[PDB]
Length: 99
Length: 99
Ligand SMILES: CC(C)[C@H](NC(=O)N(C)Cc1ccccn1)C(=O)N[C@@H](Cc1ccccc1)[C@H](O)[C@H](O)[C@H](Cc1ccccc1)NC(=O)[C@@H](NC(=O)N(C)Cc1ccccn1)C(C)C
Image (cartoon, rainbow over all chains, first blue to last red; front, side, top):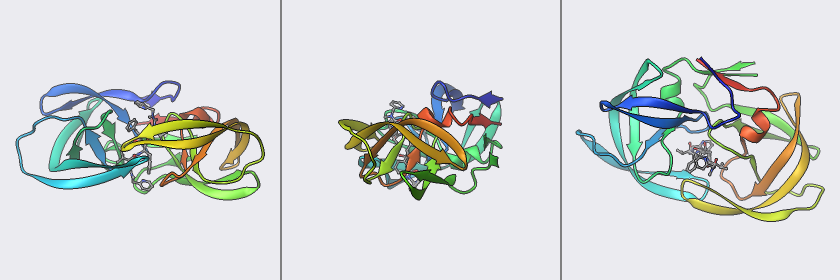
């Protein structure tokens, strides 16, 4: 598919069995998702953004499915205001920027 | 061009006379550049992201060239970690996400 950028590029992702929407984000290095409790082992982390840093938990090897396309990687869960799909999972789904 | 996202998507921009690099950022509504003097008048604004809010100066109707493509649009200047080109100028240059 081709997403245009008139609206925020939101898509549905299936993660841990359930669907959520998430923003496709070429300027994020990592994927950050709203608070949820996944089974599994995690690590504390801090990630930063325009106004400062926030505390998150890192899960490794999570399968997500972004418009039919699976990807496996690291996800950070924390008190974020949006669910953000960053480049670590976007590379796996073959996604490009074209102008 | 077609840009893959294995590395951070950074381009050279020309603005005010300067060259700079900025990130092409689909997850950003607006464009935020590090502090500079730009010709023109400006209004204070706040913008936010992960971590909170910063104070930015707003300049409207600013010419900017991203990879040899011109846009003319609003640019916010403030103390951002990174120079970000957001969706307000990516649609002028005809950028899409494809996968
Ligand atoms: C730049 C700013 C105007 C932009 N804000 C924005 O678009 N807003 C607030 C409108 C809005 C409101 C509600 C929903 C959606 N959008 C923003 O920060 N967007 C975030 C997404 C977001 C939106 C709202 C709340 C919280 C998050 C978007 O993720 C940007 O890609 C942002 C850009 C950025 C990059 C580097 C440094 C600062 C800002 N990435 C990030 O914040 C990511 N950080 C990151 O990847 N970093 C810091 C690594 C890095 C370092 C240096 C250079 C590049 N990358 C994190 C989500 C992990």
